[PDB]
Amino acid sequence: TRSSRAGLQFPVGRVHRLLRKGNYAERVGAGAPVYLAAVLEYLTAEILELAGNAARDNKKTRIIPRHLQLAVRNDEELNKLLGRVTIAQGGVLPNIQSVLLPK
Amino acid sequence: AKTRSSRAGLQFPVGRVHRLLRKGNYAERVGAGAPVYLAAVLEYLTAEILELAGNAARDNKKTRIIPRHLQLAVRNDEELNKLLGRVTIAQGGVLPNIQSVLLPK
Amino acid sequence: NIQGITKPAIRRLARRGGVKRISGLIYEETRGVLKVFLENVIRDAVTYTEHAKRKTVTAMDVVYALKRQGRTLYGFGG
Amino acid sequence: KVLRDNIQGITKPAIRRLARRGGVKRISGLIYEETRGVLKVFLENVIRDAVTYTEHAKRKTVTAMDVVYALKRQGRTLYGFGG
Amino acid sequence: HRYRPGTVALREIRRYQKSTELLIRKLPFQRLVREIAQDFKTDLRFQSSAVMALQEASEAYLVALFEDTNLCAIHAKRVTIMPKDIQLARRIRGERA
Amino acid sequence: PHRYRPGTVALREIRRYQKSTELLIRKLPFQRLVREIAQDFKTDLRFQSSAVMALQEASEAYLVALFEDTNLCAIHAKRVTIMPKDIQLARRIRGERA
Amino acid sequence: TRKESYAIYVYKVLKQVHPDTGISSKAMSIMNSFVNDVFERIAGEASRLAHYNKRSTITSREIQTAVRLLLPGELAKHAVSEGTKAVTKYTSAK
Amino acid sequence: KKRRKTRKESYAIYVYKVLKQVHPDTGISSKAMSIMNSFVNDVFERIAGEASRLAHYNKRSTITSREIQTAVRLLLPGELAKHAVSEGTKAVTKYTSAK
DNA sequence: ATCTCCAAATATCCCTTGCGGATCGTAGAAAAAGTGTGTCAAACTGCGCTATCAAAGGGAAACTTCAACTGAATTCAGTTGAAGTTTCCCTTTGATAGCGCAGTTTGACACACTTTTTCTACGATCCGCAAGGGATATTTGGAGAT
DNA sequence: ATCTCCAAATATCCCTTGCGGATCGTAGAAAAAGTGTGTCAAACTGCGCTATCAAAGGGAAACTTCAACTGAATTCAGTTGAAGTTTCCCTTTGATAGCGCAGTTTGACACACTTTTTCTACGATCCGCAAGGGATATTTGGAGAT
Ligand SMILES: [Mn+2]
Ligand SMILES: [Mn+2]
Ligand SMILES: [Mn+2]
Ligand SMILES: [Mn+2]
Ligand SMILES: [Mn+2]
Ligand SMILES: [Mn+2]
Ligand SMILES: [Mn+2]
Ligand SMILES: [Mn+2]
Ligand SMILES: [Mn+2]
Ligand SMILES: [Mn+2]
Ligand SMILES: [Mn+2]
Ligand SMILES: [Mn+2]
Ligand SMILES: [Mn+2]
Ligand SMILES: [Mn+2]
Ligand SMILES: [Mn+2]
Ligand SMILES: [Mn+2]
Ligand SMILES: [Mn+2]
Ligand SMILES: [Mn+2]
Ligand SMILES: [Mn+2]
Ligand SMILES: [Mn+2]
Ligand SMILES: [Mn+2]
């Protein structure tokens, strides 16, 4: 498998097929799906790393959508990347405006 | 009739539109009626903006359409404003509009 | 049917959005805003359903419609 | 020669003219530095993408198209300069 | 015993921001969806997840809107959201002219 | 000597600028700023003159429209004067960050 | 080299609608951006529709539902009838 | 057999693999997995979409790792972009070695 | 009420240009024709999942009671931004010259695509059992009263 | 501050169910092989970009003055939220009816593709002339003064 040659868990062969069928261009070079598979793998790692921690913090061993949302919105860069995405069953960050709290 | 535009009753170029559809990687195949339909849609939208912009030009005692007229046209029309809601027309300026509270008393 | 979106339900929505105090007129505005939101999404979702020559609105029809509106949703077939 | 502090070339009267066009009657003295900061962030974001297009094309000259493409990328489509 | 006005509201805020449950009851929401759809095309069925997709999108939308509505209320030195705050938020979002 | 009341000239400035379409930021200054910001991303860049004009068209348009939203925020708070907090409220609701 | 534009067609449609009105160079460049932009938006949406439905071809049906997704209200209605009328007239010939 | 339900494809196994790499003792619910699959699909479409425009803009017929790279630079915010460019460059370097 | 006066509007003169309308000659692309081929329409079908039904209980929504605390109005004064004036910085304008580099071009080929055969990864499907659900009890964090 | 007193957080324990691993079976990825064209590297080149200077003068900066704006402070009517009672309808559970989605097969014909003919649309170029648009002087609408 091309994934093994590249050091990746994500499927270089599937990614290549999907690029060929998505009508992005006439031709796809051989490095393209490797590069792309690697980037998709890196981002799923980045998200899963922070969500795992949010699961830990919430005293749970299973990542649920809430932990994915916590991870995303507490992370400046992931929050930007997913700035127009809604995670189903994620809820919101705990946030109360100062002026609403009693003195 | 020779040209496909002529056959379709169209000013816009059916053959160019077909080629542009084929060379834009939109799908493997383009059907024969696709470029006719799209050429016609493009022609219609250009007629609509040009009509409204010529009227703006005349409102302004002018004989030639400049970007300002295109802008006045687009933003005084609800549907064109919406279609071009995220578009900037270079040298268009804005519509005359002062909020009430800012006028003297 | 729009009245099935009750005052308490709208209050709960507002609480999640961080609202402490709500004018009596909010409940009617909200219903109008939600109606507009649903009409726009459902309009598009139904255009997709019809284009596929189907009689059944799929979650994908909704997902694609939400994507068109710049309201991408994860969790239902993205 | 070194370019520095060129944001200060976005003068107060210039910012005031833009605000007039935007319909603004009265302007706080604090607006001008707020506006500079905002413009800086706007240009950094568009220019950053525009330069990425230039680099990709193996060119050393930022073309109008690199900017038009960057503007489109940012949901700020511009008409009048090609494309 | 009586909690002061706002104390229970504040408790409620804390409660709902910790959870992820849909806050509109499921059946009234379903009826609304079907009524709106009928207006566009008669004789439609829905996948159950289609309705759920719409409810998740709708609530996400309204919650975020109330966040912006709240900021506009606060901007005006008030603590109470009013229709005008919704209208200002929607104007700035470019949802409304 | 004659003196217009405060706000009279401001109103006529609005009318003046709302009628015209010319760029309102001096041209060489804008071009230096562009060039400085670009150099911080890549040294040795040249610019087509139309590239800089496109950026000035977009920038002024962005800022005019932000000033419209800012004014609505000021009016909402029962003022006629735009303040930094109006621009901030406007950018926050737009989803603009940094 | 050749720079292709929609200019001559925009000129023609302008003469139909406003026979004694000219158009400035910058106004025309704007009209060219406009036509290209709408082409892109429509072709893009049509592309998605064929993919979503597993078809290999963009037909006028894809163009048509793309038009209905993209254009508001009255504008979609008239574009649809202009588009359908043109496909009808075109098939009627060969 | 004979009549076969169409095979659905997802990223679920590679996501679970990566999850074991980063959190050996952490699991994932099926709703969370669905979100993760949407994420991967959304990001794939966004990147290949730029790469496609890039090739078109430059009159080229091929999407190469170069288009993927600049597309990642357009799409991703600062640090994420830096890290994704490293990882993509390294995978490509490693892959072209392995013959 | 009525006059004074400032700047935007209107009127006049010349004049640079940038438009529509030419004619040109010509590259490149569209149309025309001929043949190859794979997409998708239709028809028949099987069954997943959508709609529906009947009932019942329990909790949510609606309604009612009360008054706390909020939004809105009023007044007023220090703060501050607008208007106008004066000085002169540095932008604008125009024109020159040098060359950096964008864009065209042409041979060689490395790389991607297409085709066919073999191999094996990832899909569907299955279910023991551990994480989380749900119920009950106890502890802890505060809010409101005195 | 200190005591009362709610409600959320935490603890504890038994039940439920969907995670996650294991099993079988194939669609799709890889290997191998033969084919061509897009890409790349290298040669030459003239557009327009950088730069620079000069001359003039438009507009920026920095000042004084003070009008009127912001916002602080105060007041209170009433619209809110909290907690009571009453009324309604959502959800849950167990299928049964059957719509219409989606699986399978197929050959006609719509669309590809490649070659030759026809003609559109481009780039280069002069031309009449209203269309502005800049420089110079006069009248006008109304803001502010008397
Ligand atoms: Mn029916
Ligand atoms: Mn620098
Ligand atoms: Mn780890
Ligand atoms: Mn001309
Ligand atoms: Mn030829
Ligand atoms: Mn108050
Ligand atoms: Mn009141
Ligand atoms: Mn004071
Ligand atoms: Mn001051
Ligand atoms: Mn000075
Ligand atoms: Mn070069
Ligand atoms: Mn447990
Ligand atoms: Mn529990
Ligand atoms: Mn305590
Ligand atoms: Mn599972
Ligand atoms: Mn196979
Ligand atoms: Mn070579
Ligand atoms: Mn001056
Ligand atoms: Mn009272
Ligand atoms: Mn049937
Ligand atoms: Mn008079």
Image (cartoon, coloured by chain):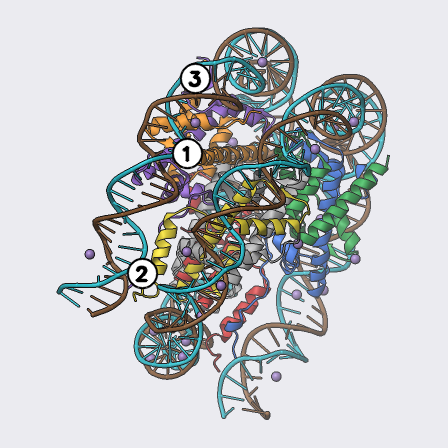
Chain colours: A blue, B purple, E red, F yellow, G orange, H green, I cyan, J brown
**Amino acid bearing label 1:** Ser
- Image quadrant of residue B73? top left
Q: Earlier in the sequence, mark 3 or mark 2?
A: 3
Locate residue E58, reporting x and y percent. Answer: 50, 53
Q: CA distance from mark 1 to mark 3?
A: 31 Å
- Marks 1/3 in contact by CB < 8 Å: the verdict is no
Of discs 2 and 1, which sits in the foreground?
A: 1
Quarter of the picture containing the C terminus of chain H is: top right
Q: Which mark is residue B103?
A: 2
Question: Numbered disc 3: what chain?
Answer: B
- Circle 1: is it few (<14), some (14-19), or many (20+) Cα within 10 Å? few
Contact, CB < 8 Å: mark 2 with mark 1?
no
Vertical relation: G89 (above or below) J71: above
**For residue J25, side relative to residue E60 (left or right):** right
Dot 1 corresponds to which residue? G24
Please identify, in this view, whether the residue under mark 3 or under mark 2 is nearer the observer: 2
User: Which residue in the protein does label 3 denote?
Assistant: B7
Mark 3: give few (<14), some (14-19) or many (20+) Cα within 10 Å: some
Q: Give the x, y percent position of residue H98.
A: 86, 37
Chain that bears disc 1: G
For marks 3 and 2, give the CA distance.
Answer: 58 Å
* Res. H61 image quadrant: top right
